[PDB]
Amino acid sequence: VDFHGYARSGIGWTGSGGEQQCFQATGAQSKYRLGNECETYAELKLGQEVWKEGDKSFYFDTNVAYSVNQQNDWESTDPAFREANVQGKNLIEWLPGSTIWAGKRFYQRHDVHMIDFYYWDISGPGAGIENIDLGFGKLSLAATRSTEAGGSYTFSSQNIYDEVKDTANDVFDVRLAGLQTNPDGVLELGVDYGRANTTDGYKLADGASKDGWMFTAEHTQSMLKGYNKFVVQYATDAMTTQGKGQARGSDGSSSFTEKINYANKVINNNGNMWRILDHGAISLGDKWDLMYVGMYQNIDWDNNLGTEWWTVGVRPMYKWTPIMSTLLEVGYDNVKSQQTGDRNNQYKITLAQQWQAGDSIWSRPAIRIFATYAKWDEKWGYIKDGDNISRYAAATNSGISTNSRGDSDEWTFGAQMEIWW
Amino acid sequence: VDFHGYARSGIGWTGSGGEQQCFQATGAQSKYRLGNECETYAELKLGQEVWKEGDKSFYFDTNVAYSVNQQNDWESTDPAFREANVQGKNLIEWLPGSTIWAGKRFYQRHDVHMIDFYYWDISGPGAGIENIDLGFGKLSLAATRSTEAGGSYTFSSQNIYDEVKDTANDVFDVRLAGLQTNPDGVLELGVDYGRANTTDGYKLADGASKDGWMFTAEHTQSMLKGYNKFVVQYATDAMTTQGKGQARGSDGSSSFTEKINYANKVINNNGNMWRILDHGAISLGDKWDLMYVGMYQNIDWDNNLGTEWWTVGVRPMYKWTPIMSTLLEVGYDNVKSQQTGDRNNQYKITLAQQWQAGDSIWSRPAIRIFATYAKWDEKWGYIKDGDNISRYAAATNSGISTNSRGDSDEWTFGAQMEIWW
Amino acid sequence: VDFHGYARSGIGWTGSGGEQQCFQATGAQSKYRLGNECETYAELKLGQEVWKEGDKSFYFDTNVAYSVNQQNDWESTDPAFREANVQGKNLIEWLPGSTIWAGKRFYQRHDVHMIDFYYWDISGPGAGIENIDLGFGKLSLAATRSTEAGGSYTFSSQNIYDEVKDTANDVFDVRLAGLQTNPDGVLELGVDYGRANTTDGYKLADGASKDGWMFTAEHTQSMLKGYNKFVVQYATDAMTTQGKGQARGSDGSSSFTEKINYANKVINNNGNMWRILDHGAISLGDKWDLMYVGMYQNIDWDNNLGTEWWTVGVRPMYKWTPIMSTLLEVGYDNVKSQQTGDRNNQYKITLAQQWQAGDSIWSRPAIRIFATYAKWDEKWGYIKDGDNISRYAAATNSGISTNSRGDSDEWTFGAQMEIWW
Ligand SMILES: OC[C@H]1O[C@H](O[C@H]2[C@H](O)[C@@H](O)[C@@H](O[C@H]3[C@H](O)[C@@H](O)[C@H](O)O[C@@H]3CO)O[C@@H]2CO)[C@H](O)[C@@H](O)[C@@H]1O
Ligand SMILES: OC[C@H]1O[C@H](O[C@H]2[C@H](O)[C@@H](O)[C@@H](O[C@H]3[C@H](O)[C@@H](O)[C@H](O)O[C@@H]3CO)O[C@@H]2CO)[C@H](O)[C@@H](O)[C@@H]1O
Ligand SMILES: OC[C@H]1O[C@H](O[C@H]2[C@H](O)[C@@H](O)[C@@H](O[C@H]3[C@H](O)[C@@H](O)[C@H](O)O[C@@H]3CO)O[C@@H]2CO)[C@H](O)[C@@H](O)[C@@H]1O
Ligand SMILES: [Ca+2]
């Protein structure tokens, strides 16, 4: 049996008191993770090549995830059963080298490690055929599913309904990778079309976006014993909410019962998204490794409830010895509310001493001892409707109750381990 | 460590819209599974032979099961811890070859794969000694437990009680296997006696069945590079509800509080069950394999709330190549309500293209692409008491709200993987 | 992958009726386990030495625990994710042989097997450096965390608060082990300082103990092919509730809302605890093994709600053959309520026939068939406030509703397996 996975766990303190606190800018879809992770997360994968005959084989893979708050020894949880699929390699004679698969699977995910941000992730239940050799590149086709809560109604009279149902969103994915564009440079193109797919008799409330498209272009350049990836993505309507390739076609739906059930008008995700990303990991000589990110993301919703986000960060690693190093991470986030026009910003600086299994910025396991400082100035926040957070924003100053963190700073410190195997 | 288990996962669509839907005749205890399974189910077993000295050994086995709806990537669930037992082989000198065991264990289960129907399954917490060599056959003795919710009350006066408690049901199982009845034919006999076992002070409500018996005779005939199993089973009272060997002695109990607690009259399972089953798997030459089932089951309850069920099905497999085949599954169900006398029927046809690790209808893993068509005509259904389904039936036409699916049809299609290792 | 763990599972019956019942003296923190365990408990550990280079290595370990009531086959549960840590050996050149670690971990726990009682257990999220060689002994430093529910309030005026929060309790642990005091005798000394650590803005209600100390001295003497451990521990205030090294600094807090939130005065754990323990496992010749415990524990609280507990037990094993033996366990508990001055007592006798993987009282797996008899006389119980048990006690006779079991006896019998691997 093959044992693989990922895990992080630690203990931390907040300078002003109590357990460690993690800092993320209101409106930003991520945070600079070094010394800024507040939970024990673990994925335990058990897989096996169950059959092999010649060039043909069947591989079975699983994945059970656990997330606990690391507050005590005994911590109960509901594990997420994320993967359970079978991959058959070389079974289709006329499509030599291709792999056919079916089941729940993390499918060709693309992420930026330092901000733990996935920008191309259509994982979930699915099926497809990958690595079809076109000579000049590899073609991959796949269909996966996601499901939204509610959104499908059996309308009796106009917007009064009898029953609600969860809405299945299908995604059809096509990717062409390995296009040699220049020496040591490769290009991958991808298209995603997603849509809400309602059960017969059910319908989406008035105004649901229904569907959308997403286009991705990623260029990988090998250099400095590492790489640099340049990404450009454009998403449309239903693909703007999740923003990684999964469709949210009934996003914004709601209803109220009095007992006559009324399906409110959908406060939809019609609009578009532009993401220009550039990240990499390179070696600057014998003693230095460097990870970096630079991203501009603009979610332009017709309804004007979107955000414009800028994030930049850098993580240099100095190698004292092959197993010991000092890491520094500096990250900056600036988010502008499309609705109010105000801006929120945060910058965090983390200094960590580390012992890792190898001399790479990518070597894991790693045991860290760190100190983090975060300073933020948030001029807006989402209107906190009691306990639930609204899609609407309000300036911190306007007496409205928002989830804005205000203007402040804090520092934390502690120990942590991270590992993938 | 030994890694074993079972898993199925896939993605599907309903011809008329939305996610895949699965078809089972109202009143039937199973359904024809090919291209008619709607969840990701997986059992991960990790076991080990922990000690061995000569012919003696101790084997430790576990089993953790997961069932998720395959609607998204992240799906939390409460896994069922189903097995955790130790088996000691050859420890009893005077009972050479026998195995003694204790713990939660899937104990000698008998099922029909194509309809995923278990007909002899007393699994659960238990202990026993199996494979005692009698020369002309093997004797096995076991005691397992199951528990019903409520059913035990501390009666103060009449049907008024202070406290309720869950009811333990003990099963005492005896089996004699390996009786050579004819060339290539073997017979196994089994007897099960089960009873609700109340805690001192507690009592079952009026009408509870309390105990029952079940008798099983299974003949296995080796032929056509496969087999044919003929089964005859007769169950009495408490053994008719589950119908596989576990006792439901307080089945039908209920109470209402106003705060004076009243234990209603138990609408018991007194009566009998007859099951005549014939299923098999054989090879018809080089290119054909075939699975088939034929079953008649009659649950005759004193209260007339039972059912008479007929099910027949066939699953031929045509081998294009050693790893690729086309499967067809045709199954028919007919259920007569003992109460109303009405009949429900369904027939489903499934066509699937498959790639499997081997050339047997039993080879797994398997990756399938299928299309299913189901047509049904249901004249009755269980009275849907609001959201909960009642033990009482009503004709579809009688204005009463039942769970009957009426007269209709549907078709689905998708991809799925199934594997046992 | 390294597979390790612990598991127990069985089936039992109570002489007077129904499932097996387990016997523990009201007020006692443990019970004599042989044939007196009523659940299936299992810990499945999957670990791996993920990197090694010379004398340096990184070991990754995990632990997922399950506890089910063994009442049925399918039993859903929320597993506890208890361990996920990395240990790096020999990474600090100037502290040769020491191991640094971070993550959730069972850290150097000390327990008495036969009563399943842990007396030194600060396990949980943490980090530390162990086995620093001092020549005359080994030094270990660690910091772990535990969390209490509520206990931290944002007070607006007096004892009226806006928000509550869970309270983090930090423990700083120092141990010196391996002090050679006499031939075949070794001594370990340990100090624990724990304190509630509140988030800025939050405060503990009035009267909270806030912090405390615990001192441990354990002497191990090797003899009779086994050992004898003599332990003396003294705990103070916040360390008296859990009593194993973890801090409960806001223990006793409560609040009531009317909506004005009032934080009641903390019914604290100020006081002290004395624990004098002596346990061991030795071999008396070829046919006899013996486990024994003797303990006096006195929790003297200022609020007079503590207990004085005496427990003594013996478990001799007679070896019929190398894999078969007869075990007898006799245990006695006597608990005096500090509050009422009344005493509760229980004695249990267990006789078991066992088959184990080896000839030691410590050999596992083991399959047992047993019969247990327990007789108790409880003069007091904790005031059962409806369904919840209070910190206050009352004599059984005083018409007050307590959880006292009265004066009675019972006997059970069954089969069970236990294993650690
Ligand atoms: O294994 C390869 C990748 O491993 C690392 O990715 C980790 C993330 O660091 C970790 O946060 C976690 O991400 C999940 C996230 O926690 C969860 O809330 C979200 O819903 O799904 C995320 C995807 O699982 O797990 C992944 C590994 O699965 C590493 O950061 C990355 O660079 C590697 O490519
Ligand atoms: O492993 C040998 C058997 O494997 C297969 O049986 C599977 C079933 O196909 C699968 O549905 C599942 O059955 C369980 C069912 O899903 C659950 O709801 C019920 O409560 O318990 C059932 C028993 O576990 O798991 C079994 C494997 O345990 C195969 O179909 C069968 O022919 C093989 O003998
Ligand atoms: O593995 C070494 C130890 O194994 C055995 O200890 C078991 C206990 O017997 C078992 O009850 C369980 O204890 C846990 C308890 O059930 C749980 O409720 C509590 O919160 O935590 C306890 C610690 O896990 O698990 C331990 C093993 O972790 C054996 O009894 C002991 O002597 C061995 O040292
Ligand atoms: Ca749960």
Image (tube, coloured by chain):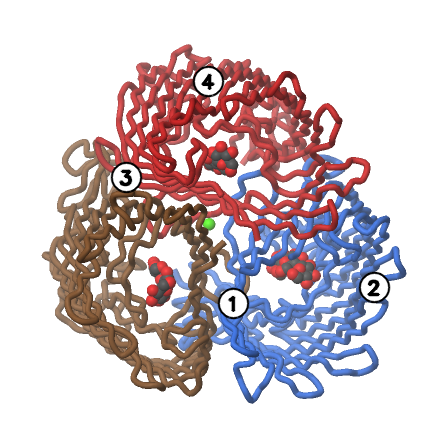
Chain colours: A blue, B brown, C red
Q: Name the residue under label 3.
A: B165
Q: How far across and down, in percent of the image, does residue A74 sit?
A: 53, 40
Name above or below for residue C406 compared with residue A95: above
The answer as to whether the residues below labels 3 and 4 share one chain is no
Left or right for C369, reference B249:
right
Distance from disc 3 to disc 4, alpha carbons, whole Å, reads 37 Å
Q: Mark 4 points at which residue?
A: C294
Kind of residue at disc 4: Gly
Say what secondary structure mark 1 lies in: strand
Kind of residue at disc 3: Lys
Q: Residue A282 carries which label?
A: 2
Distance from disc 2 to disc 1, alpha carbons, whole Å, reads 34 Å
Q: In which quarter of the image is residue A339?
A: bottom right
Distance from disc 3 to disc 2, alpha carbons, whole Å, reads 65 Å
The answer as to whether the residues below labels 3 and 1 share one chain is no
- Please, which residue is most extreme toward the left here? B302
Tag 4: Cα neighbours inside 10 Å, few (<14), some, or many (≥20)? some
Q: How far across and down, in percent of the image, does residue A314 sit?
A: 83, 58
Distance from disc 1 to disc 4, alpha carbons, whole Å, reads 53 Å
